[PDB]
Length: 383
Image 1: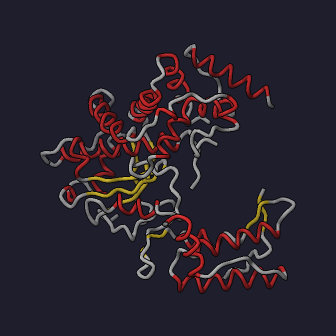
Image 2: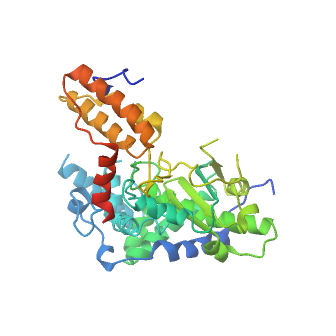
C-alpha cells in the first residue's frame, strides 16, 4: 500500500566448532550474560500476560502495548505447548509468545543500553549520548557489523539458552518453563523489529561476542578468560546489528578481523556494513541507520539518518484517503531528521523539500528552524 507523494521526483584453525567441545564455553557465556541482562529486574514485570493484556496491553510498563477465533487458537497453542507439542506457524503464535515473553522484553527495555540490549533506544533523547558513553568506555576503538547464520549447529545451542534466561527472569516453575522453550522453537518461523527475533538476536550478539573473546584469547596465547570480557569490551546490539568497543590492550588480538573469523567457527558471518579495517572511531560507524555526531556548538550527541534514507522519505506515501497529509508529514519528518545533521546540510535540503511541497500543493510545511528543532529536543529529553 505505497504510492508516490505530491513531491515525488522533485528532490534533487580453519575448521568449525561442534556442540560437543563448546558446551562449556556456551554455558559460561550464558552465565556472564545473565549477570548483565537481569540487572535491574522488578518483580512487577515477572508475570505472564493475558490474552487481553497481550492483545490490548498492560500498564505495568510503558513498553507493554477473528476475535474469539484468534483467542481460541492462542488457547489451543498454549495447551499444545503445555503438553510439550508444537503447532504449525503465525498470529496466534505472536500473541502466545507475547503472553509468555513480553514481561522479560519490557524488563530489558527498561534497563536498556547499559545491559547491551538497545531495544527501546529513543534516538533523539539522551539515549544516543548514553550509548556513546557505553561505546567509548574502554578506548577510542570500535567496530560495528551484523551477523548471519550459515550453520545453525551452534546457533541452536545458544538459542535454547535464551529461553533459559527468560525462564530465570520470570521464575514461574516447570510448566511455564516448557511453554517458553516450545514457543521459542518457531521464533524464526513466524529501526522497528518484532518482539520475537530481535531480543533473541540481541542475546546471540551478547553471547557470541563473549565466546569470540574466549576463542580469540586462546588463539593468541593471551592469559585471559571469558571472565575478563568485562574489563575490555563494551557493546550494544539491536537484533543482529552491533557496535563493539574494545580496550587498546586487547586491541591487536580481538579486533574486527579476528572476531569475524571466530564467528565463522561458530557458524556465523560477521560483516562490516561500512566497507575491512581492524577497528574504527565512533564517529565513523553507523548504527540503526544513523551515525554518532557531536555538535561542536550545542555540545550534544545526535543521530542523523542516512542521507539516502532521508531524501527518499518525502518521495512516498501510504495509499489511502489522505495523500496530501502523507506528503506533508513525510516532508516534515524528513526535515526534522535533517535537523540532527550538520547545519550546512539542513539549510540545503529543508529549502528544497519545503519549496517542493509549496510549489506543488499551494500550502506550506509546518516546520522549525535548525535551532528550533534542537531546542524542542533539549526542552523534552534533557532537563
